[PDB]
Image (cartoon, coloured by chain):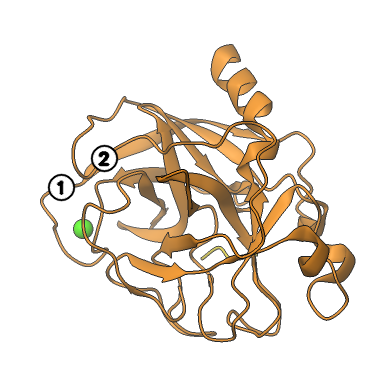
């Protein structure tokens, strides 16, 4: 996940 | 955003910075899209941690006073009830934040246009990702809001073996994968803006990249498909  | 360019201050007025309290200061952690004067759409995974969050609208540079920012606390967090932090690939990476105050609209602060329910983009559709996320794999956040052109990769291709395989679901949008341009940590929760019939609309909520790296060829950035959740979004706003 990208997020921080 | 890896391989981005600095956005003009007024290009993406629905983009917000979601920040958490860190010591005596605030730290950017995720993006979001302002969808009502008192509601922000973001990624569920951005709000798994038990942090104090605030939203900044009218933000451009995280490291300087732009003279346009409005800072507002988060009053309520509604995560999609099917979200499972253990399973980002299952989907449902979406959450709505009710703001403590309604923000004031202007050139820097506008509601994001959402697609009609069920809308799917043709392969190779023009979109931009925006955000303050890392500018390189294992890099650092951007100071100024960045944008990168990421054309969509349709489900048939994205879910093929050399791309994302079974990891990608039809409730997601894939975009990019050129090996140069991509979302990266810190962009999560923000918008993918795609041009349809002359108007940009927010078709994605940034969700994940490959564990190997942000800009990896044939691992396009993956977004929650906004048009899969229109009813959910309406129901949350109506019941809160
Ligand atoms: Ca600023």
> Mark 1 near ligand 1 (CB under 8 Å)?
yes
In the image, residue B211 lies at what x, y percent?
71, 78
Foreground pick, B184 / B28: B184
> Is B40 situated left or right of B107 in this image?
right
Query: Quick one: SS at disc 1?
Result: loop
Estimate how packed mark 1 is, as few (under 14), some (14 to 19) or many (20 or more) residues with alpha carbons within 10 Å.
some
**Up-down relation of residue B153 to residue B196 (above or below):** below
Disc 1 sits on a residue from what chain? Answer: B
Residue at the farthest top position:
B239
* Place of residue B176 in the rendered image (x, y in percent of width and height, measured from the top left): 59, 72
Give the vertical position of B103 relative to B60 (above or below).
above
Q: Do the residues labelled 1 and 2 touch (CB within 8 Å)?
A: yes
- If the picture is divided into quarters, which one holds ligand 1? bottom left
Q: Mark 2 lies on which chain?
A: B
Q: Which chain is orange?
A: B
**SS for callout 2:** loop
Residue B154, given in percent of the width and then of the height, sits at 72, 61
Residue at the left extreme of this rendering: B67
Q: Where is residue B110 in the image (x, y as percent from the top left)?
A: 30, 37
Q: Which of B152 and B50 is in front in this view?
A: B152
What quarter of the picture does the N terminus of chain B occupy?
bottom left
Which tint was used for chain A?
yellow
Q: Which residue lies at the image location 64% right of the left edge and 46% below the top edge?
A: B44
Tell me, for residue B27, which label it has, or none. none
Spatial CA distance of label 1 from label 2 is 9 Å
Query: Which residue in the protein does label 2 denote?
Result: B109
Reading the image, the residue beneath label 1 is B68
């Amino acid at each position: 996940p990208i997020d921080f | 955003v890896v391989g981005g360019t600095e956005a003009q201050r007024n290009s993406w007025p629905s983009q917000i910075s979601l920040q958490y309290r860190s010591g005596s200061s605030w730290a950017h952690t995720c993006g979001g899209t302002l969808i009502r004067q008192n509601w922000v759409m973001t990624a569920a995974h951005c709000v798994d941690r038990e942090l104090t969050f605030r939203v900044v609208v009218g933000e451009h540079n995280l490291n300087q006073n732009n003279g346009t920012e409005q800072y507002v606390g988060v009053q309520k967090i509604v995560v999609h009830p099917y979200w499972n932090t253990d399973d980002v690939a299952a989907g449902y990476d979406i959450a709505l934040l009710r703001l403590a105050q309604s923000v004031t609209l202007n050139s820097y602060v506008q509601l994001g246009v959402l697609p009609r329910a069920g809308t799917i983009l043709a392969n190779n559709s023009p979109c931009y990702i925006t955000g303050w996320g890392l500018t390189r794999t294992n890099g650092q956040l951007a100071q100024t809001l960045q944008q990168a052109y990421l054309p969509t990769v349709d489900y048939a291709i994205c879910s093929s073996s050399s791309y994302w395989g079974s990891t990608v679901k039809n409730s997601m949008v894939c975009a990019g994968g050129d090996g140069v341009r991509s979302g990266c940590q810190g962009d999560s929760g923000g918008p993918l803006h795609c041009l349809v019939n002359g108007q940009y609309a927010v078709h994605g909520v940034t969700s994940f990249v490959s564990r190997l790296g942000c800009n990896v060829t044939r691992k396009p950035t993956v977004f929650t498909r906004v048009s899969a959740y229109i009813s959910w979004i309406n129901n949350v706003i109506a019941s809160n």
